[PDB]
Amino acid sequence: NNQGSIISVSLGPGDPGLITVKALSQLREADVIYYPGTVSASGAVTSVALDILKEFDLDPSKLRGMLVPMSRSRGAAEASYAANYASMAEEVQAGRRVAVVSVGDGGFYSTASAIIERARRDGLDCSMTPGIPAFIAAGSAAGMPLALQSDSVLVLAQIDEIGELERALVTHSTVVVMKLSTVRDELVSFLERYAKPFLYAEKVGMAGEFITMEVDALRSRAIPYFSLLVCSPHCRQSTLSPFA
Amino acid sequence: MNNQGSIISVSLGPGDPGLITVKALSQLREADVIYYPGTVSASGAVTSVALDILKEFDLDPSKLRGMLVPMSRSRASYAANYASMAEEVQAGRRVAVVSVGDGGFYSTASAIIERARRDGLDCSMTPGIPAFIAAGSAAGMPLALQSDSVLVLAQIDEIGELERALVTHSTVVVMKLSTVRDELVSFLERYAKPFLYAEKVGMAGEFITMEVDALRSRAIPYFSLLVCSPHCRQSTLSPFA
Image (tube, rainbow over all chains, first blue to last red; front, side, top):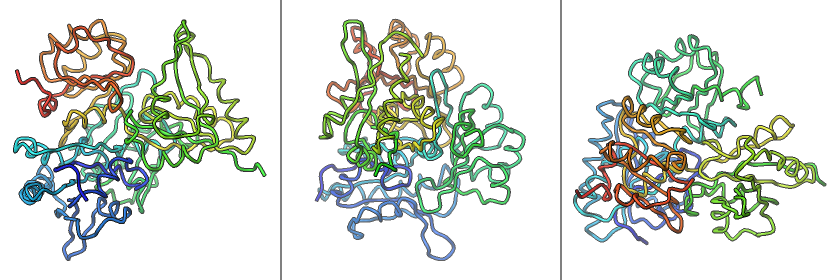
């Protein structure tokens, strides 16, 4: 029926089997669940978060979409989440158990952190249940390690110019770049230039999963928001590598 | 029949048995045999966070097989747990090899997976939540926002590694803080900025702090990490001072 007041519930990165035992139980006991999604020109919502929730046989009545276009004002998501907080607060006032869900982990580049600021300063009971980051899941779906003994790992997100990844590469073991859409027109020439093992992973664990280590397989590919890149020598270990 | 016989690298997550994925837990319950890592001191005392997590799931205890490695002969030198696995696999059996955290992220399992894979075996990987991700959520802080970077180090030799990295990176996580235990308090005094220290997150004896004074007498164990980040001031733990 309920338990907490405001909970940031990580869904994991797309495969519903990769939610935690705890996150899943929190969802089933929540009174209301807010999820992010995007809308196209017509209606037609796209929401990876909702696609995941739909696998849990939850009461479709308790679900509250927070909807945006495709935008980059520190992700119009911040305003969208901000705008939605009032209702979440009133639900919490009504004595309800509110979940705000995140693809991957709620504390790792998630706008849910805006809800947990406000929740904590308005003195409400709030919590974070963590989830598997997308880059962790990508490494495992490719059958490779991301980090071994003495490695460093640098994680970047919303890369500005492709030159930012280029500079980082040499001073770091593995580099991970999230949200590749922001360099969708620069990715392929970067990859030809780099000429070193990489993992491209899109929609991992989800219906349209696509993972590749071949530049040719990306030449005429649309690079969407939910996609990431791993540049690392360890990519040689993957099942997707000729090196075995 | 024996023509099956598989091996899976199953991540356990960071410590709280509630932070196992639904899928990894199902795989452990289905497995015929479950190998877990652990270490053994000279007086023969066994330390194994992995077995401590397994002990929380109601598994058949006769299914569990320790892969214990002396804290000594570094490769240790005991990859010879695999021939055992292969045999079980040869015998038609479902073998799980487990990892604390994620099995691809500074893990004990990678060297086993590579051996399986040099051999003809399929060894899929089920992911888990790394300890540093769990530590952030336990403290109620985010680890990264909009265009932030995250740098992860582990088993660092010397405290300078960290100091140096923090000149040019805002958020730096260091895993296996034991390696710099003698230097931690002094480092944190001169650092004089928000930090999160976390030990046994999600388990009995969880200890997390953003107070240097809570560390002055503390035994900093091997499964210990530090996060240095301004994001630490976004926790009810960040010094009321």
